[PDB]
Length: 95
Image 1 (cartoon, helix red, strand yellow):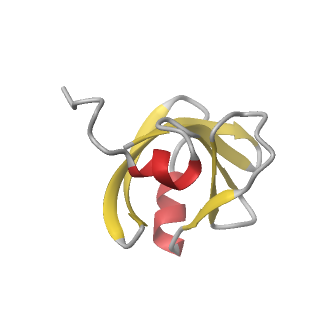
Image 2 (cartoon, rainbow, N blue to C red):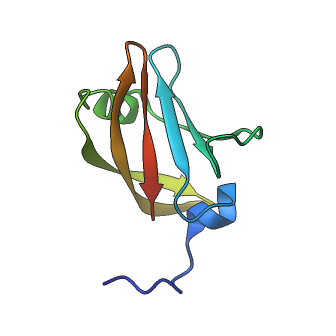
């Protein structure tokens, strides 16, 4: 099992070890929020292919792992979630 004391670059970047994420149908900016009520706006600009990969998720929960560049370092980010509405995907992330 991963050691929970391993430095977590999501925590350093957006303020949560397991942030909530959202990806719309009209933008390739991945939103990372420390809470579902948070008002700030940490984003990761996904490439078109990365965003298309998230959008293969259906309305049933599944997982996709993306290699995101945080602080110039490639971090495997594990996105669990689903298509939550006609035009939005959302879930929780870990890293």
